[PDB]
Amino acid sequence: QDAVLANSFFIMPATVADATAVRNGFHSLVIDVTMALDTLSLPVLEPLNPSRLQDVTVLSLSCLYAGVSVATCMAILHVGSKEDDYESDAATIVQKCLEIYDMIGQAISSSRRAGGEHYQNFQLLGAWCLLNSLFLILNLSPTALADKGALRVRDILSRTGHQGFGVLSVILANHAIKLLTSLFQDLQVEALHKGGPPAALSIMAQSTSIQRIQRLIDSVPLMNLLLTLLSTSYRKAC
Amino acid sequence: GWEVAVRPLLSASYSAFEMKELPQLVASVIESESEILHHEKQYEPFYSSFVALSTHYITTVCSLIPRNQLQSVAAACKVLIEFSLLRLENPDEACAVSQKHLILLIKGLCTGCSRLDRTEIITFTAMMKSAKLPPELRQKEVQMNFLNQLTSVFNPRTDQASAIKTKNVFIAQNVASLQELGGSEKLLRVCLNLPYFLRYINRF
C-alpha cells in the first residue's frame, strides 16, 4: 500500500541480513499464503463492489508483492553467497502468489459488479509490480549487496542485469509478459486505425490505454528491462 | 489481358482454382487495385461481378495455398474487404453486388468460408461474361511475390491440420485488414443505417 503512492517499487528483502531474516521468515509465510489461498477459493469475494473490490485488489496485489520480495531475497541469496527446505518453501510461496493474483483477476473479470476498465487496471497494477520486481532482481550484484551490508527502481534509474535472475525469476517474468501482452493488445485496437498523465496505481483509477502503458514505461526502462531479460535468459539456457 | 484475367477466373468457373492461375489472380487484383477502388465508370457491372466471384474463389482456397501465395491471397482479400466496405458505405445502383451479398463476402473472408450458393455464383459469372469491361510473365509474377516477401515480414503467429492453420492465418489476416480499414466501424454505421431498422430504432 505504501508503494501505490508511486514511491518506486521498493522490495525490502534485499540487504544480505534482511534476506537471511526473511529465509528465517520463509516457512511461516508459506503457512499464511496457503491459508489465504484456501480461504479465497470459496465465494469469499462474490460481490465485487467498489468498496469490497478495493480490499479484494488489496489482498491480491499483497501476495503479488510478498512473492516478488521473496524472489528478490532468493536472488540476494544466490548473488551474495534445511536450506533446500527453505528453497522449496519460497518456491511454493511465489507459486501461490501468482495463483492468488490470477484468481482475483478472473474474479474481477467475470464479475457483474466489476471488470472492463476495473479489470484492466488490476492487470495494469499487477504488471507494474511484476516488472519492478524483475528490474530489482536483475540489477543486484555481489558488489551492491556487500556495500549495503529497500531497493528503489527510481534509485537505480538515477544511478544509471545478469545474476539474481533464476527459476522463480522466470515465473514472475512469464506472468509479467502475459499482462503486458494484454495491455498492449488493448492499446492496438484502442488506436483503431491509429485511432494524459500516467495511470494512477489504483484499481478504479480511470486512464486511457496509452496511459496505462505510460505508467508501465515510466516505471522501468521497458525496452531495457525486456531486452536484458531476453539476453540473460538466453545466456542461462545456454 | 483483362480478358485473360477474367479468364483464369472462369477457368476456375469451370472448377476450383487450380491455384496455378491463382498466382495470376492475386496479381491482377493487386495491380488493378486502384482501378476497382474508384473507377466510378459504366464498367461498374464488370468490375463488381469481378470483385464478387474473386472474393468467392479466394475464399474457396484458404485451406491450402503456397505460404507465399498464402501471403498473396491474404493481400488480395484485404483488398477485397476494402472494396466491399467501400461499396457498403457508398450504396450504388450500378454496383451489381447487393449489400447482403457484400456483407457475406466480408464475413466469408473473416470466417474462412464462402456462403454464396452456386446459383448466386452463376448469376455473377453470367453478369461477368455479359459485363466484361463492357516466361516473362512468370518472371514478373515472382519478382512481385518477392518484393512482397522482402518489404513485408509476415508472422505466422500460429499435414491434416495444416490446412486449418492456413485458414486460421487467412482469417486473422482478413480481420486485421478490416481493423486497419476501420471497416468494423463502417459496418456498424451500415447496420444502424438499415432501411427497415431505422423505424424500430427511432420507436425504441
Image (cartoon, grey):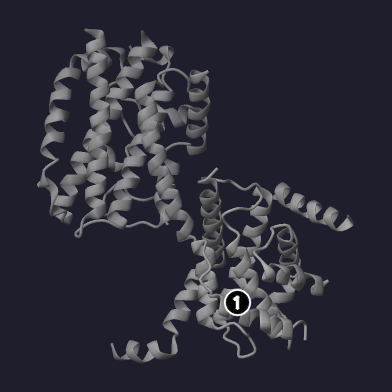
Horizontal side of A142 relative to B114 (left or right) equals left
Tell me if residue A193 can be seen.
no
Q: Nearer the viewer, residue B113 or A63?
A: B113
Q: Residues within 10 Å of mark 1 (few under 14, many from 20)?
A: some
Residue A163 occupies quadrant: top left
Q: Total number of numbered labels?
A: 1
Expressed as whole percent of the image width and height from the top left, the position of residue B174 reads 55, 61
Horizontal side of B64 relative to A178 (left or right) equals right
Q: Circle 1 — which element? A: helix
Residue for point 22% across, 36% down: A62
Residue farthest along the top direction in this orientation: A82
Residue for point 37% across, 25% down: A169
Residue B105 occupies quadrant: bottom right
Expressed as whole percent of the image width and height from the top left, the position of residue B39 reads 72, 81
Residue B83 occupies quadrant: bottom right
Q: Nearer the viewer, residue B174 or A52?
A: B174
Expressed as whole percent of the image width and height from the top left, the position of residue B103 reads 51, 75
Kind of residue at disc 1: Ile
Q: Is residue B43 above or below residue A103?
A: below
Chain identifier of the residue bearing label 1 in the image: B
Horizontal side of B162 relative to A111 (left or right) equals right
Quadrant location of the N terminus of chain B? bottom right
Residue with the mark numbered 1: B121
Residue for point 56% across, 46% down: B156
Q: Nearer the viewer, residue B16 or A236?
A: B16
Residue farthest along the right direction in this orientation: B136
Q: Is residue B108 above or below residue A21?
A: below
